[PDB]
Image (cartoon, grey):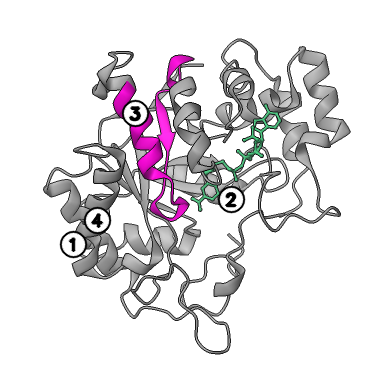
Amino acid sequence: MASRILLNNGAKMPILGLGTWKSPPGQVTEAVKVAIDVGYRHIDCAHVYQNENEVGVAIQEKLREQVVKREELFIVSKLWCTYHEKGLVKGACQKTLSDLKLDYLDLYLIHWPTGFKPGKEFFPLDESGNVVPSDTNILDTWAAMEELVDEGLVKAIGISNFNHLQVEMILNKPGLKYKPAVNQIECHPYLTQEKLIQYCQSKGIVVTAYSPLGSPDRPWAKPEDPSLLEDPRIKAIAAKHNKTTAQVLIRFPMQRNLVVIPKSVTPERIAENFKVFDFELSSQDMTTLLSYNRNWRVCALLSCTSHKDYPFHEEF
Ligand SMILES: NC(=O)c1ccc[n+]([C@@H]2O[C@H](COP(=O)([O-])OP(=O)(O)OC[C@H]3O[C@@H](n4cnc5c(N)ncnc54)[C@H](OP(=O)(O)O)[C@@H]3O)[C@@H](O)[C@H]2O)c1
């Protein structure tokens, strides 16, 4: 298992990163400092997580402390849906850069294919509860992303939560200047994503798997929901390999040539989750884990199911 994957912009991306959604602002600075101390070189961020300033304090301290060089870090952030307009993308990117204390991002993603009305609210509502869309389409927002590469603000651009028709729309864009480097999608044994992964990989797009542990801290969790970390079948694979269930769930996407971004703010778990470069799941184990697919999503963007660009009506 090599530690980095080559992207279609010629840069290398670490295959294991630290997620930061739901990491409290008073804990995430320590989480990121611990992560860099124990070997993580990739941090996954987003403006909508409301904690980039605190992530940036950790990054800056470790760069100042010469624990790591900027060229060795791979920092990812994401353009939120209320900034898809051509004239707002640069300022959104620069706010993220200012918060993270960076003068460039390694990778900047369109967070969702759905544009929303600009304004202070991240989910602007009509008086009945539906998301108010933007009329800007995915192709014009992609051209604005391409401008960020040409201005030196980001080294690579990509997409997140795009279905295969939407990836194809980008690839078929008239005048396309830069292909997406990455599609970041939910992926774990209950949402195995074979068709969309195959498609992206065949096009040279690297896939990043989010919520690899099934996001047990997601806000909308219901007791009745399936639970990866408690599934006795997965616990049995882990026991056979003398690893934790989380370590099996992180190694699984790595062996599919995916990048994976488990989140923790607990120092012991941050270190445990990185200790996945020293064992191998067999092909039988991989096929067994794939067999647990049930098309179950943590993140279904349920307030946006009538948006023209809602991604999850499509079979993949
Ligand atoms: N592009 C998108 O739309 C999108 C959507 C969702 C997620 N993401 C990204 O993907 C990252 C990961 O997904 P996620 O945050 O949904 O969830 P996740 O990584 O699947 O699970 C995080 C949860 O697992 C717990 N945990 C971590 N390591 C553990 C271990 N070794 N043993 C037991 N429990 C453990 C964490 O607890 P503690 O933190 O308390 O330790 C937290 O409650 C996000 O943080 C974000 O960066 C992106």
Say which residue label 4 marks.
145
Within 8 Å: ligand 1 and the Cβ of disc 1? no
Is disc 2 surrounded by few (<14), some (14 to 19) or many (20+) residues within 10 Å? few
Q: Nearer the viewer, mark 2 or mark 4?
A: 4
| Foreground pick, 169 / 11 | 11
| Foreground pick, 113 / 69 | 69
The label number, if any, that marks residue 195 in the structure image: 2
Q: Quadrant of the C terminus?
A: bottom right
Q: Amino acid at mark 2?
A: Lys
Q: Nearer the viewer, mark 4 or mark 3?
A: 3
The x, y position of residue 33, in whole percent, is 43, 23
Q: Amino acid at mark 1?
A: Gly
Q: Is residue 287 left or right of residue 269?
A: right
Say which residue label 1 marks.
175
Q: Nearer the viewer, mark 3 or mark 1?
A: 3
Q: Amino acid at mark 3?
A: Ile
Q: Residue at x 26, y 37 (%)?
A: 101
Q: Up-down: is 120 above or below 168?
A: below
Which region of the structure is painted magenta?
A: 36-61
The reply to whether dot 3 and dot 2 touch (C-beta < 8 Å) is no
Q: Up-down: is 64 above or below 250?
A: above
Is disc 3 surrounded by few (<14), some (14 to 19) or many (20+) residues within 10 Å? many
Q: Is residue 99 left or right of residue 246?
A: left
The x, y position of residue 119, in whole percent, is 34, 74
Q: Residue 133 falls in which quadrant of the image?
A: bottom left
Is disc 4 surrounded by few (<14), some (14 to 19) or many (20+) residues within 10 Å? many
* Nearer-N-terminus badge (4/3): 3
| Foreground pick, 91 / 56 | 56
Q: Residue furthest left?
A: 151
